[PDB]
Image (spheres, coloured by chain):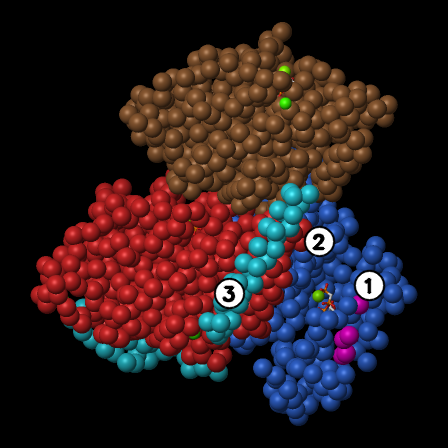
């Protein structure tokens, strides 16, 4: 057994983390007070669920998690929430005033004064680990804390934990729910600084989740609560292999080995099916073939893009529920004769498949209906570069006029960091095109 | 198709299906960057207070 | 009030479409870089498809299918026909072609060339590429063709027995305009054009062998003698087929043309369809056909950004607004729908 | 707890400031004695932004009242909510400022400014995490204009890392007290260009035209003008006073609204403006909110381009329909929004509507058309300054003509900077 530490940064990271740990407890049978009756080894153990939960002598199962935000109001919700008893105060770190949607304010000005406290609280969790394998970091691209403090934290983590893997769950900005005009700046600034420090990053575009909630859950105007419950389902299916018995993606290193052959190209596309409204009294349960075919529909992807006009480097299928390998292979054979699935020539055309018999857990009273089987596909396709092109274009429009740049320079950031970060993204877009286009 | 590396357990199973064969900055350096930005903030504030003194 | 942007000033077809949209009083033209548009008349090269369909509250439509270049390039069309099981190498309506780089089929072309010369049969081939604007060599010697390319090209069998119009004993080719809407309905414009050579066909000068409108207007002394602009329309051509060959344009030629158009576009439908996509596409195509002396139709070229005949600009462009634009953005048939199974 | 310290200076500043506190006390359920008597916890969730909590669960406005004569502040203390203010926060002299920016900034005001800063310091010292200041004042008089800008400069010196926000009433010959108002306004505008992060431009010309043309008031009074200002001030501060995601504090608002530091002068707008029981639909709220007749700066937005826009909807309504209408206005008139700032229009919705209305909308625009306001003041300035008319009132207080020439050039530079980004 090897422990994993989750770090939740800024409002988006904290609220998504709260939804994930709520779901983890429901999946593992952990009560809001931390008790877990199915766990017969009181006060210890090296089971698969112990990668995410430590144990006290009283039988409380405590998340291996740190929450960090430069404003106290969001984390105060965790302090007085349903699962408040899971966490002790040392895991919840709050500042007085936030980064005001300013990467430079979160990274330089406020980050310099709180980085040592955050690392000390992470060190306390690492000291409880007999074999820590690394970190999962949840944050937004657009916020000042999620962008600016995360990049500083990721730099320091590479220094203090040089051999440890680091995975990201990153929220890509969408104007339908965004709260700042400068979010394209913050997204590109934090991607540039974090790129060399992240081994594998799962980007989630709020635009895709918003439309999935509207179209498949019949929510007229989705809130963060609707979005985060769906995101936590995708995150759960991604991390389930670390928390349950199995042989695929059983450690953080295997995520890079299975999904990231080229280190800079470490942004796998996630596609999830089925998303079914709980308001429907009776819904026809989708087969293995139907949910697998849905993994190749852009309407089900965490980022809207067209994988037909790119190339695949790796593909993983993560099933939960009533699924047997025979039906998976039969579904894959039919799909290959209808879909445009092109792998790069230096990679084998294939799928790594993992099946967990336990069907997905839904939050009682939530928007998502219980289904007999579901699947999350993780594919490293060059088509996700469309998201970088959208972001870099908005950056270019504002930076050509130096709009809002004075806010960043006023925090001690040099203007050259803008163009340096943009040049890095230009090289990133060129890498994707060299890999996926003939 | 070819199915390889089939592993089975009580809670599920995993395998691989093949359709076709193929064809860091130091702690000191980070500290210098944070202090350099703080020094630029101090310089900008000193110039403002000088301007207000005039 | 719908909004649109214009990003290809050199397009004569969509300059008329844009003129028609403004004349409706219900469409407004924005700056070419304004992202809050309903319709994009995009550029030919590197159209930013990845930035479409990300504007909240705007149904967005573009006049090009991403990926349709596979059909509209010389080397890409040859590879698509040979490698697709729907079309296969046994495809009967496409001339025997090979992709030759200056993946490479040099030995395959020489194998069939040596097989023809040994068999005492017709062994004339034509070399061309997508870079040929007004770069084509017709020869019976394979050594002369391979040496010309080294100076990505394709070499296909030159149809040595074309259907020759009389009087004149002259060559021609048939252009068909095809519109594919956002639902992937295939509409064949009822009006085609025969771009005719004004010189007599000599099987022993590229002016009588190449039916391009620019070549006939720059090298043929008989330009405009038989028909205006070396363009014969379907009404006269159908009358000729009845008087000369006792048949109709529909029976002898158009059935094959509709079959070829349907086959090509259905083959690439899974790769380019925008059915469940966050933006929608339509596109106007220009299919070029050859007819041999036995009334067999051969596909030669698919143009992704075709122009139109001067007499047919008004009718066709209005038809574009009707079925491709107003079907998505309704305001306040000249096409033959080639039915198919999606 | 991100506290804001409020300051009101001069006759206009104290009269609109008192009405602002009357309006938002009613919205938060605070009675004239400081006791809460509301029925929604949303009234108290962000109450500490503007109110200190005293003994007996009393709520005291974090407000400081300044004037160089006691007249208007005596009327405030005798007003409806006069007893709600902290008595020690009344700081006043006796000489007055004679509608003279020099008296407010250099002579009379200099004698009183230290006592104001002592009160500001006491309020700031009790703040958990002070986010900044808001000042209400006019630019056409002497105390609000001259001493108000003096106060801003000294507050910036003592609190250089805090946001400075102002509600600045611009003079107009249509509603004028003295002929020297263009002098006082031009001198003050340069101060605001340097020392505020956000300034709401409230044009008395616009307020008069709205009362007369729209509200059908043939003889508008200052009280009628201040009713529009109160409603506007309540709307633009809604995002600071109630839970929300967008522009929840003064710094995030500035980061969203100010792409270039000097161009921080906003055109506010309000809807509905009814001369009264009829329900107003979301399309009507949105169209009226963007109409020039609902703007408070007397500038035509179609004569310029929007750099940034903040919109706040209040009341129980369909947020789906709000999003659709806000997208409609942008997609209908996309030429009036600069294309080099993508998605520059942000929308907030608060469930609690203002008093007497089921639904309302407030508009905050950073438009290049605001240069028409500064051009208007600059022309009136030059018409007098070219003949050095009325300058003796100012040179008698120690000012030199060169300071007027520099203020003139400074505002013409501001106009040219707006014209740069309009092209
Ligand atoms: N999916 C999702 N996105 C969120 C959530 N909260 C904020 N966001 C997105 O995150 C971006 C804003 O970043 P935040 O996380 O709110 O900001 P922050 O990290 O707290 O940083 P500062 O507030 O500037 O100090 C916007 O694009 C929001 O749409 C959330 O709970 N779920
Ligand atoms: N295999 C073949 N057999 C006989 N004639 C041929 C032929 N290929 C081409 N031709 C003749 O040569 C001409 C030029 O062929 P090509 O398809 O390259 O035109 P082009 O691409 O230069 C202009 P367009 O885009 O309108 O077709 C054709 O119009 C046709 O008359
Ligand atoms: N809207 C509004 N404007 C006012 C009010 N009182 C004065 N003004 C304007 O303010 C300017 C006069 O400044 P004033 O505040 O009276 O002088 P001060 O006491 O020295 O600051 C003129 O332009 C007046 O039109 C008021 O109650 N409401
Ligand atoms: Ca145990
Ligand atoms: Ca590392
Ligand atoms: Ca004195
Ligand atoms: Mg925050
Ligand atoms: Mg061509
Ligand atoms: Mg007065």
Q: Nearer the viewer, residue C101 or D105?
A: D105
- Label 3 and label 1: CA atoms lie apart by 56 Å
The correct choice, above or below, for D77 with respect to A286 in the image is above
Residue count near mark 2 (Cα–Cα under 10 Å), binned few <14, some 14–19, many ≥20: some
What residue would you read off at disc 3? A193
| D373 drawn magenta | no
Where does the magenta region start and end? Answer: C134-138
Circle nearer the viewer, 3 or 2 = 3
Is residue D136 placed above or below A132 in the rendered structure? above
Badge 1: how crowded within 10 Å, few (<14), some, or many (20+)?
few
Chain B on-screen colour: cyan
| Left-right relation of A43 to A267 | left
Mark nearer the viewer, 1 or 2 = 2
- Judged from the image, the secondary structure of the residue bearing numbered disc 1 is helix
Q: Dividing the picture into quarters, in which one does residue D27 lie?
A: top left
Q: Colour of chain A?
A: red
User: Which residue appears at 55% of the width and 68% of the height?
Assistant: A428
Q: Chain of mark 2?
A: C
Residue under disc 1 on the same chain as residue under disc 2: yes
How would you classify the magenta stretch by its main secondary structure?
loop
Q: In the figure, what tint was chain C given?
A: blue
The x, y position of residue A163, in whole percent, is: 37, 77
Q: Which mark is residue C8?
A: 2
Q: Residue at the location (65% across, 43% down)? A: B53
């Amino acid at each position: 057994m090897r422990e994993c530490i989750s770090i939740h940064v800024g409002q988006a990271g904290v609220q998504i983390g709260n939804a994930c740990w709520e779901l983890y407890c429901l999946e593992h049978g952990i009560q809001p007070d931390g008790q877990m009756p199915s766990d017969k080894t009181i006060g210890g153990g090296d089971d698969s669920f112990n990668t995410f939960f430590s144990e006290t002598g009283a039988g409380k199962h405590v998340p291996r998690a740190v929450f960090v935000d430069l404003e106290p109001t969001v984390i105060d919700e965790v302090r007085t929430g349903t699962y408040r008893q899971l966490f002790h105060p040392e895991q919840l770190i709050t500042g007085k005033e936030d980064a005001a949607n300013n990467y430079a304010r979160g990274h330089y000005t406020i980050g310099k004064e709180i980085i040592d406290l955050v690392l000390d609280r992470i060190r306390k969790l690492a000291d409880q680990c007999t074999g820590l394998q690394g970190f999962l970091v949840f944050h937004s691209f657009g916020g000042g804390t999620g962008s600016g403090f995360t990049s500083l934290l990721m730099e320091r983590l590479s220094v203090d934990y040089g051999k440890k893997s680091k995975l990201e769950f990153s929220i890509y900005p969408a104007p339908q729910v965004s709260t700042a005009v400068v979010e394209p700046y913050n997204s590109i600034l934090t991607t540039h600084t974090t790129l060399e420090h992240s081994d594998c990053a799962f980007m989630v575009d709020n635009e895709a989740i918003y439309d999935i909630c509207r179209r498949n859950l019949d929510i007229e105007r989705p809130t963060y609560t609707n979005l985060n419950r769906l995101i936590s389902q995708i995150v759960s299916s991604i991390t389930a292999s670390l928390r349950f018995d199995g042989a695929l993606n059983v450690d953080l290193t295997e995520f890079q080995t299975n999904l990231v052959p080229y280190p800079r190209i470490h942004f796998p596309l996630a596609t999830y099916a089925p998303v079914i409204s709980a308001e429907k009294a009776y819904h026809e349960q989708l087969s293995v073939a139907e949910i697998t075919n849905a993994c190749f529909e852009p309407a089900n992807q965490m980022v809207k893009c067209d994988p037909r006009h790119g190339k695949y480097m790796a593909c993983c299928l993560l099933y939960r529920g009533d699924v047997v390998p025979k039906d998976v292979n039969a579904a894959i054979a039919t799909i290959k004769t209808k879909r445009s699935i092109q792998f790069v020539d230096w990679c084998p055309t294939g799928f790594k498949v993992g099946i967990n018999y336990q069907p997905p857990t839904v939050v009682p009273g939530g928007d998502l209906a219980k289904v007999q089987r579901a699947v999350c596909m993780l594919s490293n396709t060059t088509a996700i570069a469309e998201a970088w092109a959208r972001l870099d274009h908005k950056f270019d429009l504002m930076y050509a006029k130096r709009a809002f740049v004075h806010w960043y320079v006023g925090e001690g950031m040099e203007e050259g960091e803008f163009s340096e970060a943009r040049e890095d993204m230009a090289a990133l877009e060129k890498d994707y095109e060299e890999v996926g286009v003939d | 198709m070819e199915v390889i590396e089939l592993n089975k357990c009580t809670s599920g199973q995993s395998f691989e299906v093949i359709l076709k064969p193929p064809s860091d900055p130091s702690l000191e350096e980070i500290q210098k960057k944070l202090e350099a930005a703080e020094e630029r903030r101090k310089y900008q504030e000193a110039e403002l207070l000088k301007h207000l003194a005039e | 009030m719908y909004t649109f942007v214009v990003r290809d000033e050199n397009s004569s077809v969509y300059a008329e479409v844009s003129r028609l949209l403004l004349a409706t009083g219900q469409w407004k033209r924005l700056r070419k870089d304004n992202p809050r548009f309903n319709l994009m008349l995009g550029e030919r090269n590197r159209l930013p498809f990845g930035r479409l369909g990300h504007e909240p509250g705007l149904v967005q439509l573009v006049n090009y299918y991403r990926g349709a270049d596979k059909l509209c390039r010389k080397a890409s069309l040859v590879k698509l026909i040979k490698t697709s099981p729907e079309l296969s190498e046994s495809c009967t309506w496409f001339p025997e072609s090979y992709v030759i780089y200056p993946t490479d089929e040099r030995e395959v072309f020489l194998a069939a060339y040596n097989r023809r010369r040994e068999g005492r049969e017709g062994n004339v081939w034509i070399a061309k590429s997508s870079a040929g604007a007004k770069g084509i060599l017709i020869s019976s010697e394979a050594s002369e063709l391979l040496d010309f390319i080294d100076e990505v090209h394709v070499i296909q069998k030159y149809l040595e027995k074309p259907l020759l119009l009389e009087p004149g004993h002259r060559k021609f080719d048939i252009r068909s305009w095809v519109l594919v809407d956002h639902l992937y309905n295939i509409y064949l414009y009822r009006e085609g054009v025969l771009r005719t050579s004004s010189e007599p066909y000599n099987s022993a000068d590229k002016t009588c062998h190449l039916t391009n409108h620019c070549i006939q207007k720059e090298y043929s002394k008989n330009y405009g003698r038989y028909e205006e602009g070396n363009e014969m329309f379907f009404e006269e051509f159908n009358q000729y087929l009845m008087d000369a060959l006792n048949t109709t344009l529909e029976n002898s030629i158009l059935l094959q043309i509709k079959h070829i158009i349907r086959s090509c576009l259905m083959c690439i439908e899974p790769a380019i369809s925008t059915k469940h996509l966050h933006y929608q596409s339509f596109q106007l195509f220009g299919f070029d056909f050859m007819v041999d002396e036995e009334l067999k139709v051969w596909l030669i070229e698919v143009n992704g950004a075709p122009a139109c005949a001067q007499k047919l600009y008004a009718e066709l462009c209005q038809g574009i607004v009707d079925v491709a634009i107003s079907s998505v953005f309704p305001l306040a048939s000249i096409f033959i729908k080639l039915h198919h199974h999606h | 707890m991100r506290e804001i310290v409020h300051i009101q200076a001069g006759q206009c500043g104290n009269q609109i400031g008192a009405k602002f506190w009357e309006v938002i006390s009613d919205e938060h359920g605070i009675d004239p004695t400081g006791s809460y008597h509301g029925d929604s916890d949303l009234q108290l969730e962000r109450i500490n932004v503007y109110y200190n909590e005293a003994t007996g669960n009393k709520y005291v406005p974090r407000a400081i009242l300044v004037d160089l004569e006691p007249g208007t502040m005596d009327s405030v203390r005798s007003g409806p909510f006069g007893q709600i203010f902290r008595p020690d926060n009344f700081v006043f002299g006796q000489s007055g400022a004679g509608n003279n920016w020099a008296k407010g900034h250099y002579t009379e005001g200099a004698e009183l400014v230290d006592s104001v800063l002592d009160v500001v310091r006491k309020e700031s010292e009790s703040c958990d995490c002070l986010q900044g200041f808001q000042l209400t004042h006019s630019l056409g008089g002497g105390t609000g204009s001259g001493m108000g800008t003096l106060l801003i400069s000294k507050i910036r010196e003592e609190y250089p890392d805090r946001i400075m926000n102002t509600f600045s009433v611009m003079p107009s010959p249509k509603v004028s007290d003295t002929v020297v108002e263009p002098y006082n306004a031009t001198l003050s505008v340069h101060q605001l260009v340097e020392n505020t992060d956000e300034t709401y431009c409230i044009d008395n010309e616009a307020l008069y035209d709205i009362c007369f043309r729209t509200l059908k008031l043939t003889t508008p009074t200052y009280g009628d003008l201040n009713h529009l200002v109160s409603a506007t001030m309540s709307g633009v501060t809604t995002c600071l006073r109630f839970p929300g995601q967008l522009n929840a504090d003064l710094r995030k608002l500035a980061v969203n609204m100010v792409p270039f530091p000097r161009l921080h002068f906003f055109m506010p707008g309000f809807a509905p403006l009814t001369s009264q029981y009829r329900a107003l639909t979301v399309p009507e709220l949105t169209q009226q909110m963007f109409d020039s007749k609902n703007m408070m700066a007397a500038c035509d937005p179609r004569h310029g381009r929007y750099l940034t826009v903040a919109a706040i909807f209040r009341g129980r309504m369909s947020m789906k329909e709000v999003d659709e209408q806000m997208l409609n206005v942008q997609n209908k008139n996309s030429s009036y929004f600069v294309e080099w700032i993508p998605n520059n229009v942000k929308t907030a919705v608060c469930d609690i509507p203002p008093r007497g209305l089921k639904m309302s909308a407030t508009f905050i625009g950073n438009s290049t058309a605001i240069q028409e306001l500064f051009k208007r003041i600059s022309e009136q300035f030059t018409a007098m300054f070219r003949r050095k008319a009325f300058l003796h009132w100012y040179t008698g207080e120690g000012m030199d003509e060169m300071e007027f020439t520099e203020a003139e050039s400074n505002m013409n530079d501001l106009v040219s900077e707006y014209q740069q980004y309009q092209d």
